[PDB]
Image (tube, coloured by chain):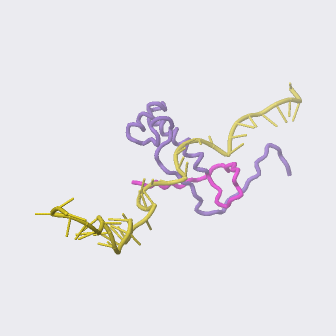
Chain colours: A purple, B yellow
RNA sequence: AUUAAGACAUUCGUGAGUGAUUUAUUUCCAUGAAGUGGCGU
């Protein structure tokens, strides 16, 4: 397999700084670095150094020398562009 | 007066004709617009 497709459900409203665009959704520049660390941690059974050695062994690293990055491409897109906008404050008001 | 005297190795003649500094090469790789509440006990 070359492509992985997943459908995400939202439980809490994300605080997004680029809400102006109608296609504003979860940013992959945030997901990918955390997912890379999560997978390397899981590959090494809770240790990121063993997990990097595992990824280094099976040629899964973009660079074998200095980064945790894994060689995959991540894209997050909206299917239906209808969204709910929330005002989140720490003060009650009518 | 003597196998002697006279006689430009010279005339004409394009280093010229054909020819792509071109072919191959991702300005790309890594990166959280995030962190924290405080006081009125």
Q: Position of residue A41 (x, y in %)?
A: 49, 35
Q: Main secondary structure of the magenta part?
A: loop
Percent across and percent down for residue A36 are 51, 41
Residue, x 79% and y 46% (percent of image)? A89
Residue B17 higher or lower than A19, as above or below: below
| In the displayed structure image, the side of residue B17 where residue A77 appears, left or right | right
Quadrant, the N terminus of chain A: bottom left
- A14 falls in the magenta region: yes
Camera-nearest residue between A42 and A13 = A42
Position of residue A70 measured from the top left corner of the image (x, y, whole percent) = 47, 43
Above or below A59: residue A94:
below
Q: For this rendering, which residue is in front, A57 or A25?
A: A57
Q: Residue at (48%, 37%) from the top-left corner?
A: A40
Which residue is at 51% across, 37% downward?
Answer: A67
- The region drawn magenta spans A1-26
Instruction: Decide which of A76, A14 is in the foreground and name it.
Output: A76
Q: Position of residue A43 (x, y in %)?
A: 44, 36
Image point (72%, 56%), residue name: A85
Please count the marks in the image.
Answer: 0
Side of B13 where A20 appears, left or right = right
Is residue A81 in the magenta section? no
């Amino acid at each position: 397999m070359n492509q992985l497709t997943a459908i995400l459900k939202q439980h809490t409203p994300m605080i997004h700084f680029q809400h102006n665009e109608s296609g504003a959704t979860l940013r992959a520049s945030e997901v990918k670095p955390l997912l890379d660390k999560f997978i390397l941690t899981k590959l090494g059974n809770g240790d990121i150094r063993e997990g990097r050695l595992y990824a280094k062994k099976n040629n899964w690293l973009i660079d074998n020398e200095k980064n945790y990055a894994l060689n995959y491409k991540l894209s997050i897109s909206l299917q239906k562009k209808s969204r709910l906008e929330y005002l989140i404050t720490s003060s009650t008001f009518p």
